[PDB]
Amino acid sequence: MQGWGKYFYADGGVYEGEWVDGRMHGRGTYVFPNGNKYEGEWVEDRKDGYGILLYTNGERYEGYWHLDKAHGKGTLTFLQGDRYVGEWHYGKKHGHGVLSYSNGDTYDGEWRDDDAWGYGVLQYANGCRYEGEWAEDRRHGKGLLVLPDGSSYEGSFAHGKKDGPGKIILKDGSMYIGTWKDGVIVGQGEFRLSENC
Amino acid sequence: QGWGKYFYADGGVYEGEWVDGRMHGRGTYVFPNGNKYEGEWVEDRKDGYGILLYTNGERYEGYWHLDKAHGKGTLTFLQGDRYVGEWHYGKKHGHGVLSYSNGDTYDGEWRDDDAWGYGVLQYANGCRYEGEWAEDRRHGKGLLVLPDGSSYEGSFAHGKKDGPGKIILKDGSMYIGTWKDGVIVGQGEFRLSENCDL
Ligand SMILES: [Cl-]
Ligand SMILES: [Cl-]
Ligand SMILES: [Cl-]
Ligand SMILES: [Cl-]
Ligand SMILES: [Cl-]
């Protein structure tokens, strides 16, 4: 099973490409029973190296594979509108990458196991903008959130909501210092105004 | 009855109309003080219109009753302070405006020579207080506007912020809480004018 050739039909899946020893090896294409079609490099019956897989619904990945999963630098385009360009780790967004959301949001930062995780900045379509840490695809740890007004909160976050100590600075110049828990003010706080009189 | 001048042993002088041996009618009296009164008299008392000029500088011009300021009258002070309003037997009482030399000027109610009731005070530092007063001090519900453009409205006690109140800024974002002796106390809530996501 050497040279070029065509083969398979596990279902109706036809692989056509290079071969070694009954394993697909080299560049080749494979239209799978789904209708998904991978066209790239192979290493011993798994996609390994660069390759493009078109999904039947519309999706389209472009990048490096390893052991039949996305691994390395790769671009995932949702022709609905989404677009991701960055590092992968065995099928999941992992490392650094940017994502353009359909709703208008844009992310730039770290990822771990297909989730925003680590440092990253997200420019919301509504005008807010977050610059801080993440955990499990939600704002977690210290961060800075600017609001389309121009005022901002800087403090701690937990599970996507304001939580812990924090300061909120106003355009006016005034400040409120207090503690949050699950996105809500409670406890003793301090509020400084810009002008005394 | 009639007119004539008199020199008391005190050094005081009176000349003007008399009735039954009592100063009554128009007359002028310069006191041993150096104070000189010039107005209407009734039975040896300032009563009706009159001016009283003090040797130190002050000058009352208005109506008198039972030898005391009573009715509408203007008093200008040592410092330059000018009161224009109603009097009640020597005390600011009713409605009156006081313009202090420091620049502040008050316009509101009075009771027993004290700011008491509703009144507006424009501070010289650019501020304005519109609220109630008790015993010459900001007391009750009031609105305090800062030159900032923000404003505090809530309650006052003995001249300081005290009780529930709201600071509302130029943005429309507001802080809601309670005060004790002009300083923040208790738990508060801060609301933003504009926020994320909604
Ligand atoms: Cl989040
Ligand atoms: Cl939140
Ligand atoms: Cl501003
Ligand atoms: Cl006061
Ligand atoms: Cl105060």
Image: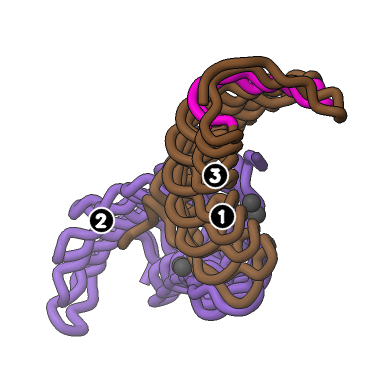
Chain colours: A purple, B brown
Q: Quadrant of residue A50?
A: bottom left
Chain identifier of the residue bearing label 3 in the image: B
Asked whether disc 3 touches disc 2, contact meaning CB atoms under 8 Å apart, the reply is no
Secondary structure mostly seen in magenta is strand
Residue located beneath label 2 in the image: A78
Assess disc 3: are there few (<14), some (14-19) or many (≥20) residues with their C-alpha within 10 Å of its C-alpha. Answer: some
Of residues B4 and B15, the one drawn nearer to the viewer in this rendering: B4
Chain identifier of the residue bearing label 2 in the image: A
Residue drawn where x is 33% and y is 59% of the image = B197
Asked whether disc 3 touches disc 1, contact meaning CB atoms under 8 Å apart, the reply is no
Span of residues in magenta:
B23-41
Callout 1 amino acid: Asp
Callout 2 amino acid: Phe
Residue located beneath label 3 in the image: B66
Residue located beneath label 1 in the image: B112
Point out the frontmost of discs 2 and 1: 1
Above or below for B81 versus A84: above
**Element under disc 1:** loop
Query: Residue A195 in the image: x percent, y percent?
Result: 63, 39
Above or below for A54 versus A32: above
Task: Kindly report the distance in space between the C-alpha atoms of the residues bearing marks 3 and 1.
Answer: 17 Å
Residue drawn where x is 60% and y is 59% of the image = B135
Seen in the image, is B7 located left or right of residue B91? right
Give the label on residue A73, or none.
none
N-term-proximal mark, 3 vs 1: 3
